[PDB]
Image (cartoon, rainbow, N blue to C red):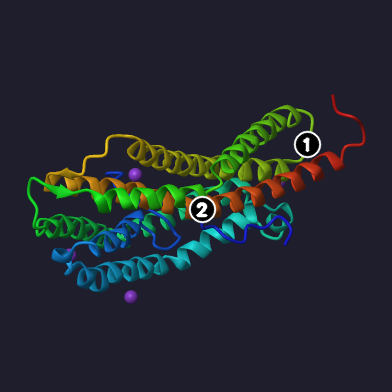
Amino acid sequence: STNTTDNIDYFDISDESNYYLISQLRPHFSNIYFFDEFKRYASYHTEIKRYEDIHKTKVNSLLNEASRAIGICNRAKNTVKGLINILENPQKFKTQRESYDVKLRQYEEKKEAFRGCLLNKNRKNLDQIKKINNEIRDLLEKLKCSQDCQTNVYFDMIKIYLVDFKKMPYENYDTFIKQYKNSYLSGVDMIRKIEKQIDNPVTINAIKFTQKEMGYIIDRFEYHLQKVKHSIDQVTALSDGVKPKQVTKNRLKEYYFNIGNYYSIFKFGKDSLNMLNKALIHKEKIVHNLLGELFGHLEERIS
Ligand SMILES: [K+]
Ligand SMILES: [K+]
Ligand SMILES: [K+]
Ligand SMILES: [K+]
């Protein structure tokens, strides 16, 4: 419907140490994608078969626990959405009595409560990530090799990842966000200019409100776009670099964690970009509609 945010999946939050980024989209942590990748690596190594058990019982548990945790925050999610829907939509704002300043304050408070819930309910889950990571490191010690560990699985995965990465329309996301930022800045500059001449506080405030959310969503989009590009570029550099047939076991652990990290961040970023792209287009529609309404009331050309 008109000028209404229907989905607020774009909010995210990281822990205080900034090691972990929590997304509202499954699997919620990029690390779960890394655990899913290591399932693949593990299948090439007879010695580390126990990972099949760890994945089934610990990784899938953690994913469900994350989903459960996120689900607990649904009432807080709805509360923020209700406030957004009032603030972005003058007609809706006009059906209640509080001042715009008061509703803004409420929104700020509930938004932080909601984001805080996404983190607080996932704290034990974050601890489980570190434990599984360490379990994987310990497990790789079981590899028969010591000084001469084969790198074929590593390089096989890199070849598969290069093909997978080509499926991402990177250039399109880049072109989109550049055009979008240009339009966004123009809209902010427009409001700075016309608000001097136009007396329509609720509509101007609604536009500013939506523009502040757009700035946040753009920031989130650029964060993931950069992460995706880094993964593509770095894994490409590995495929173009030296190709040792054999390395130490500790080195092979680092190899697997390195490409598993790049691949999981890539997948997590792909998920988020798709969602954020939709989010941005829909916010921009609201700004278009409200700017159109602002100008529609003018009886003469504004200079
Ligand atoms: K559960
Ligand atoms: K008023
Ligand atoms: K474990
Ligand atoms: K390669």
Quadrant of the snapshot with the N terminus: bottom right
Please report whichever mark, 2 or 1, sits nearer to the chain's N-terminal start: 2
Residue placed most toward the observer, 133 or 144: 144
Quadrant of the snapshot with the C terminus: top right
Label 1 Cα neighbours within 10 Å, binned few <14 / some 14-19 / many ≥20: few
Relative image position of residue 276 (x, y in whole percent): 55, 50
Q: Secondary structure at mark 2?
A: loop
Q: Residue at x 90, y 30 (%)?
A: 301
Q: Quadrant of residue 37?
A: bottom left
Q: Between label 2 and label 1, give the one nearer the viewer.
A: 2
Label 2 Cα neighbours within 10 Å, binned few <14 / some 14-19 / many ≥20: many
Q: Is residue 275 left or right of residue 238?
A: right
User: What is the C-alpha distance between the residues marked 2 and 1?
Assistant: 32 Å
Q: Residue at x 42, y 56 (%)?
A: 23
The residue labelled by disc 1 is 199
Image position of 237 with respect to 18: above or below: above
Relative image position of residue 299 (x, y in whole percent): 92, 36
Relative image position of residue 282 (x, y in whole percent): 66, 52
- Indicate the amino acid at tag 2: Tyr
Residue 67 visible in the shown view = yes
Q: Is residue 241 left or right of residue 213?
A: left
Q: Is residue 297 left or right of residue 194?
A: right
Q: Which mark is residue 83?
A: none
Residue 112 visible in the shown view = no
Furthest residue to the right?
299
Q: Which mark is residue 10?
A: 2
